Every structure is written in C-alpha cells, then in structure tokens.
Length: 264
Ligand SMILES: Cc1cc(Nc2cc(N3CCN(C)CC3)nc(Sc3ccc(NC(=O)C4CC4)cc3)n2)[nH]n1
Ligand SMILES: [Cl-]
Ligand code: NA
Ligand code: NA
Image (tube, rainbow, N blue to C red; front, side):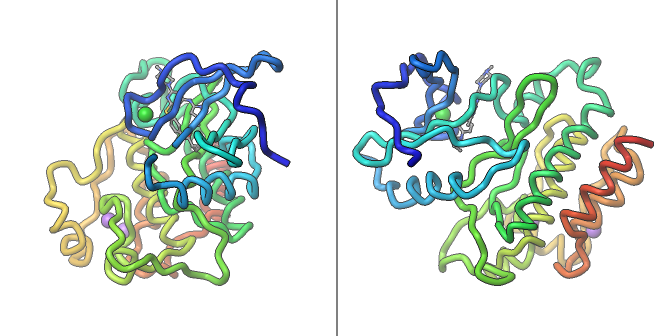
C-alpha cells in the first residue's frame, strides 16, 4: 500500500554530513514535492525495515510523516515529508536568539509534549528522544523523528537485549541499570531534551565522565537550572528526573503544563 517506484524520486544532494545514515533530499517529480529519503550492502536491513514499519503505524502533526517506502528490492527507500530547517540541536545552536525567544522555546517544548502524549496514549515508546532527533520546519514547527528504536509495547515495559549500548546522558537510570524501557524512561529523556532546549543546544552534563553519571545521579546529582529557564519549567524538568519512574509525570500532565504556560 505504501510502496512507490524509485524512479519517482529525483535525488539532488546528500543531507546531514553523514550523521543520520544515507539520507538525501529528494524531489518527487510527478507531485512536484520536496521530500527526504533515507536509504540503506550494510547489514542493517533488519532494523531499517523495522523503522519503515513503525512509521506506517503512527500519525501526528508533530511526528515526521512517512510518504512512502521502497522496500521490495534494494536500495530500500524511506520517503518522509521534508523539514527545511533540519535537526533541532543544530538549529538551536545556530539560531538568532532575538528571533528564537523564550516564547518560541516554550512553543517548541509544547509541540514535542504533544507528540509524546500521543505515543503515550498509543502505548508506544520512542527510545531515542533528544534534540538531535527532532526536526524543525516553517514557523518554528517542531516534529519528533527517527523512530529506529521505537515500539508498540505489549505491556508497560520493554527489556533491551544484553550488551545493548545507549546514549547515557539521555538514558534513565533504570534503563542503564536493568535495561528496562517504559514510557517513564521516555519521560526522563524528555527532561534532558528540555534542558537542551533551555540552553540553546548545550551538551548535557558537560565535561562529566560518562562512567560517573549513574553514580552521580544515584547520589542525587541533577543538572542545574539554565539561565533564563523559568522556575515552573525547571520544576517540571526536575520532575522528569525523579529516581523512581513512578514519580515522574505522564506525558499528558507534561503537555497540560506547557499548554497552560504557553498562555500565562
Ligand atoms: C526526515 C527529514 C529530515 C528532513 N530535513 C532535514 C533537513 C536537514 N538540513 C540540512 C542543513 N540545512 C541547513 C537545513 C536542512 N538535515 C536533515 S538530517 C536528517 C535526515 C534524516 C532523518 N531521519 C530519517 O530520515 C528517518 C526517520 C525517517 C533525520 C535527520 N534533515 N526532513 N525530513
Ligand atoms: Cl547523514
Ligand atoms: Na542518564
Ligand atoms: Na530530579
């Protein structure tokens, strides 16, 4: 149903400086439409198709939309709607802060909590929430992307395979310690994502030794409040980093808090 004919797309240039896979900007000739195209021998086919598959099952204004697949023969294609301003981390880092103000940061957070409220409702789990995995478009629209590790959950947790390796700065302690992933682990990451946004794209736990992060977190260390970050947003941010997953807010609560702030 989603399959398309590779001949349809014209591939113009490579897109990402090598950081996101083999992704090129594409022009769908017959529909006159700019699109992105992720392509894959690179023994990662199993996991590419898994990705192509999950994007068929989800649809939200703040999640990057699949337009079509070529997954009948190689090279395999993933054709998504094109976000002309790229990933959020570099956007924040390169933006004009007179244009991207505190209001715009709040808007970006609200839109992401929207995407995550929807996955939470769908009992899906993203597993790689971070500014580098969000994309920016016209009028400061932000959309969550990169669903390679995403899953529909059979119950309330998913256990990663032995020896899986994770981005530690974004990973919840129970995920580091017990390979346990849940919507509450996605909430932990969201918090770190909020800190990335608050700081216009700074690196979390700057200059800390990764092998000390768990240790520090268990002893209670958490990242300090960024300058300009409002107290309510910092309180919410800290809520996402509660040790016990149960004590963390839901994505519904979080989104309610930002929609309210976005008004007041
Ligand atoms: C998916 C997507 C990506 C985009 N747009 C862009 C745009 C972009 N830019 C490069 C630098 N200029 C200055 C800004 C635009 N760099 C990337 S880098 C990039 C490429 C691919 C993916 N992810 C996927 O293709 C998989 C999830 C389907 C993420 C980031 N993606 N539109 N839609
Ligand atoms: Cl790339
Ligand atoms: Na961590
Ligand atoms: Na905390």
